[PDB]
Image (tube, coloured by chain):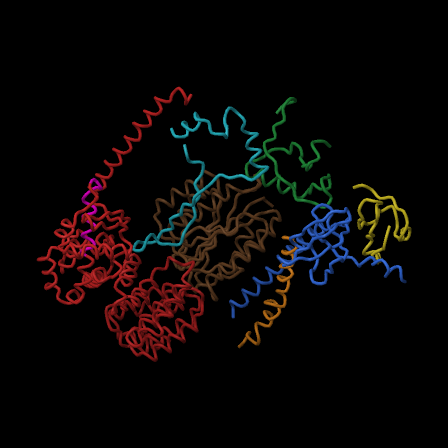
Amino acid sequence: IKIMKSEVLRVTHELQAMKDKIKENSEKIKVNKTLPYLVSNVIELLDVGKCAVIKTSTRQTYFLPVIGLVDAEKLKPGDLVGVNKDSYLILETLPTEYDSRVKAME
Amino acid sequence: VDDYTVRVIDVFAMPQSGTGVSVEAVDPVFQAKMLDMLKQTGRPEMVVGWYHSHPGFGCWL
Amino acid sequence: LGLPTEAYISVEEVHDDGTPTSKTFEHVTSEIGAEEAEEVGVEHLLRDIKDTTVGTLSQRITNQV
Amino acid sequence: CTKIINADSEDPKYIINVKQFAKFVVDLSDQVAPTDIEEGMRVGVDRN
Amino acid sequence: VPGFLQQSQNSGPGQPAVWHRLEELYTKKLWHQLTLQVLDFVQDPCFAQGDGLIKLYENFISEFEHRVNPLSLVEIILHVVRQMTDPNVALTFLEKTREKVKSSDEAVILCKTAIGALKLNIGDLQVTKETIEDVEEMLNNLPGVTSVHSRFYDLSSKYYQTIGNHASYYKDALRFLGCVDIKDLPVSEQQERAFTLGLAGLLGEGVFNFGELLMHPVLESLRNTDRQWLIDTLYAFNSGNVERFQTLKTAWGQQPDLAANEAQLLRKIQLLCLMEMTFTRPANHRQLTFEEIAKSAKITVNEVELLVMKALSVGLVKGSIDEVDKRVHMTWVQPRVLDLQQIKGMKDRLEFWCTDVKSMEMLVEHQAHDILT
Amino acid sequence: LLEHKEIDGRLKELREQLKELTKQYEKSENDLKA
Amino acid sequence: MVLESTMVCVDNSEYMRNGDFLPTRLQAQQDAVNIVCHSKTRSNPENNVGLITLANDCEVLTTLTPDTGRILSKLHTVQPKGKITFCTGIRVAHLALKHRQGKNHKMRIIAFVGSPVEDNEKDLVKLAKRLKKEKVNVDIINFGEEEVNTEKLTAFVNTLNGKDGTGSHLVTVPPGPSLADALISSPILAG
């Protein structure tokens, strides 16, 4: 019973510490995922556990062993994403622009 | 050492920041704790200057 | 001649099958290896009359000695 | 400039097309207000 | 509690001083002094048949301490359960204690090995082996206690009434001898232990030479008093001399445990003998004619091949046999203890080869001084 | 059973319910290696 | 008031297994270091505190640091499963006191011994001399065993307080009421 209370105090101190650790982690995530992302057209997703090849708007193809800082389930092969300008990883997904006639038709 | 000599005894890196390589990229707190704590280690050397890598751009400012 | 470093690791055995307790750091084979953009710094720090990676007959006989 | 990404002052980024160069999502400068920026207009953007 | 302590101050050797010390330590609520006092008290020479009141006393003491190291508390419990001498109630008491002290330290471990030791007489296999593997698998980050290993000897050694536990029993018995550094046991007890150890070494199927058996202090120090025939057998087997008359002398000097395994003992001594002939000739003439092995190992030349094959199979030598010319080639990787005079001789051999190395180094250096630069 | 009603009254939420922050830490570590 | 780096010497030995204080002598040491470090930190905000184990080895779990929460948590789960050693403990305390960060900090440690020290008076007195040469001013408090303020400890005090020197007070704690007020009446007023 007393060991239980000691474990309770230990776990609450661990909670307090890992709070600030996850905050530092988030700060450095925002340090990497700042704002001036580059949009890329995701050509397709390949299995490896998924890796994606993308065609960034700088007419350049790129293979990503890890799919950035976004979930990886929907991720349609053509879903426009904001890939990092220098390290080329997917910081965020943005809604699809248009599909030729589907915008040519209101 | 003198007006004709600068002796870079050592260098310590700095955390990568989203700004890039600027004067806001030097964390005053990180710089401090590193300075006092290296002084404790046995490296009580004043900060001579800074360095940054221009990858493939050559050497210039 | 041959002693740049020696790396040791502690193991959990008393001393042998039939001996009292000890710890007895274990030697591990050590190599001095560098990746790119570190080995080049070594070379630039070097480039005295030393090096000559290609093995001339003179250098090979010196190696045998 | 293109779609406002549905900014609402928490997503001030917009996908912008610099001619034959690429397209980028970018946030505003402090000297400009979002009310002065809407889709489809030419906007001067910094290098850094 | 003081009522029984003062009333039952008697019924114990040297009762007044010790029980008044117990009184004064109890009224002052000292426990570690109390725990050392009680371990000394239960380690007294006696039968301590007053089990009921002593178990009640330790019941109060253990319920009230709740922080005394479970090593000492479990030592007291071990002595008291040795005192009760009744299997089922002792088992239930051990369960109650291990549920009273569930600390991660060496309390449940000693409870399990005490269960195994008490259950060795009934149900040798079905419960003790799993406790053994449990103890060894969660023996970690406390190697310094060095008593659970003595109890491990107790369990896996009193398991030697088998054929397999003659080399494995020897293994954990040497491990135990390492476990108890100080001798601190009666000469008769260590003599019995070295008796069964020599038995293990001789009847060990996988143990052939296995030095450090003669060089372990526990046997060499105190086995020269009585039953020296076994130590003589150890000498002769490590020396490889069959010594038929003296080996038989020990055979009918110790009729049991050696007449019924004489075949495997002969196998072992013959392999050791071949080891010695390989030792004697320093590869100057490696090819040994079958006459040497026949006369030396006292075997027929039809059986040298068989014993060589056996020695290769077990893993001690890695030679080969030339039957055409009646020779055997030997390239073997089995070393031995090395007899300090032999240390000096091998030192001289090292000196010879090192000065040869040095001489050729100077020769090449002088001849190539033009090129070395 | 004095202070052992269900589990110390507190460990039920601290052990796993408030340990979901370790799952979020795992997510953070995936963000790291990405 | 004065800048200092405290190096507390907590005992988790097996001779600590005493009932001299009501709940637990080890817990008596835990809340005693708790209260004394509370008083010291509250006395001077920038002071540094640390922890040393003396059982079968000198574990230095927390060194000279200003924060009190983490040393406090190190007090818990101390697991008293060892054997005390005063001399090596005070040696480690002294060398840590040499390795303090701020040079102005006047050296100071808090030592709590509740076990009978098994040693020889000659080594003890020579160690008192060595600590006297380095002007390391200790306070020593006798807990636990009935040989409170043993001749070893009195010699330590009168030698470290050589002709009323550093101020290693022989504050006496009864083998009974090691009460918090009994542990704060003397030191918070003086040492």
Query: In the figure, what tint was chain A given?
Result: blue
Q: Give the chain ID for the cyan colour.
A: C
Residue B52, image x, y percentages: 68, 36
Q: Which residues are magenta?
A: E269-284
Q: Look at the picture and state if E25 lies above or below E217.
A: below
Residue E28 is at least partly visible in this image? no
Query: In the figure, what tint was chain G given?
Result: brown
Query: In the figure, what tint was chain F given?
Result: orange
Residue E302, image x, y percentages: 17, 56
| SS assignment for the magenta stretch, majority | helix
- Residue at 47% over, 63% down: G177
Q: Nearer the viewer, residue G50 or G57?
A: G57
Q: Look at the picture and state if E60 lies above or below E151.
A: below
Query: In the figure, what tint was chain D given?
Result: yellow
Residue B13, image x, y percentages: 63, 40
Q: Give the chain ID for the green colour.
A: B
Q: Give the chain ID for the red colour.
A: E
